[PDB]
Image (cartoon, rainbow, N blue to C red):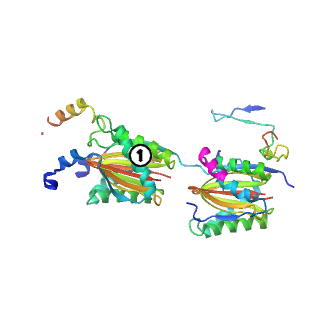
Amino acid sequence: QQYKTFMGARVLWPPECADDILEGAIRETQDALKKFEIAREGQKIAEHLKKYMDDHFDPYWHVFFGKNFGCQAVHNKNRFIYFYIEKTAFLMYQT
Amino acid sequence: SHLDKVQPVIKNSDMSVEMQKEVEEVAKKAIDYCNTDKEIATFIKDDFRSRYHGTWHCIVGRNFGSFVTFERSYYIYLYVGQLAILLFKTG
Amino acid sequence: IAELSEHSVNTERVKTGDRGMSHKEGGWPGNVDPNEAQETGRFKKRIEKS
Amino acid sequence: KAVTDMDINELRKLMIGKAIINSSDMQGDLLQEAQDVIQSGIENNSAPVLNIEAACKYIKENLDKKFGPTWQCIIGEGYAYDVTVQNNTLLFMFYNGNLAVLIFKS
Amino acid sequence: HANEQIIDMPENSEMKSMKNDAFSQAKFAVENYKFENKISSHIKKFFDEKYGPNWHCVVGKHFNAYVSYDSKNFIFFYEGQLAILLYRKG
Amino acid sequence: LTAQELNEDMPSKMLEPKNPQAPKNITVYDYYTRKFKTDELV
């Protein structure tokens, strides 16, 4: 439950996801937001992130990002990444 | 010398002292700027919304009873003259 | 098949506190109490002291 | 007689159960449930002298259980307020005499 | 009031109960638990016993998500104000 | 299983034998159980 800030993004201090992959995913999400805002056409940015994960990581990645939501899921070892950027929290688990 | 005369007093405050001091100046400025009480409520909500992002509900009346569900440490209660400046941000 | 671990993450919910107050009483100094007759009576005498 | 005989003091004394609705923004079926609960609750908690805090506490608890977790209602003799609420979540009705009631869902 | 929902479940293939169970479970679970995190765990557990494992469900009042799911195993519906999404992957 | 005292009264911290990189918890579905099973110990 102890949130930590890394590379300008707030995420769980103990990282469920791999340190290498988690940093890449956070950088990609920040770049995507810089281009497309969450508030307008928010569905498009989430879809782009999911396709990007398949290109550089194992396939069938699940990506869910919302301002307020609660979820519990089963994921592969070191395949769960949860982080908060500004007021938006992005959670992705690889299946 | 009117600003010295109003002497706005906060009966109940649930906010940081530095933030609370800023509210007193805005409250005094809003009363002189707004011709009517209805205008004062709109001005206070607009200034706070610009200063702090979120949903702000403000009600000011000579006599009223209020029970509200506001984010903790975002509710400041101040009374000047017969007007109550009450702002409570709800998520 | 890779080993699967399930983790549940929920976005923090901003706290909601319910408080009820009455502004029916007229504006008064914080030190003085509007309901108490003694506090109001002493304050009025002090004003007329000019 | 009639309206000419009637006076503001006389009208308030003559009827205390009269219900007047000034602003409606909530669905009518929802309003009927809310109107019956608020009128019954205020009279029960009115006591010897009406308490603004007492009426709001009873209304706030009943509304939270009845519809949603975060429900805010404010009642005052006179007030000016700007409130941002969800569609069909705000009902405004003032009781006979100097009693203004505002109930909204956030 | 759940004006628009996405339904992708088999009809008259004897798996018709999965759609019915999701609507019934969401209404009962959401009212009693009254927690976003708890609703996802309860809905996932009931579905897991009845139709096997590898089921992921996320419940949020407001959220945007993109995911890959097995065909005819994904149903999206709104239970009152709350929105619940449940699907089976793997 | 020992605790190192930081100088000048800093918040106390200790080292542990367990490897941090290894997954915090491993869960395997059991058909006999018929529900997801989670084992905190790894």
Residue beneath the point at 31% across and 60% down? B39
Main SS of the magenta part reads helix
Crowding at dot 1, Cα within 10 Å, few <14 / some 14-19 / many 20+, comes out as some
Q: Position of residue B18 (x, y in %)?
A: 42, 47
E89 up-or-down from D100: above or below: below
Left or right, residue B23 beside residue A1: left
Q: Position of residue E15 (x, y in %)?
A: 77, 59
Left or right, residue B89 beside residue F18: left
Residue beneath the point at 75% across and 54% down? E55
The amino acid marked with disc number 1 is Val
Q: Residue furthest right?
A: C1
Residue C14 appears in the picture as rendered:
yes
Which residues make up the magenta segment? E24-37
Q: Nearer the viewer, residue C47 or A75?
A: A75
Residue A11 appears in the picture as rendered:
no
Read off the residue under disc 1.
D37
Q: Nearer the viewer, residue D9 or B46?
A: D9
Number of numbered discs overlaid on the protein picture: 1
Q: Nearer the viewer, residue E4 or A35?
A: E4
Which chain is indicated by disc 1?
D
Residue beneath the point at 64% across and 60% down? E77
Q: Residue furthest top?
A: C38
Q: Nearer the viewer, residue D69 or A57?
A: D69
Q: Quadrant of residue F11?
A: top right
Q: Residue furthest front?
A: D1
Residue beneath the point at 30% across and 52% down? B28
Q: Secondary structure at mark 1?
A: helix
Q: Position of residue B88 (x, y in %)?
A: 43, 50
Q: Position of residue E89 (x, y in %)?
A: 78, 59
Q: Is residue B17 magenta?
A: no
Q: Is residue E35 magenta?
A: yes
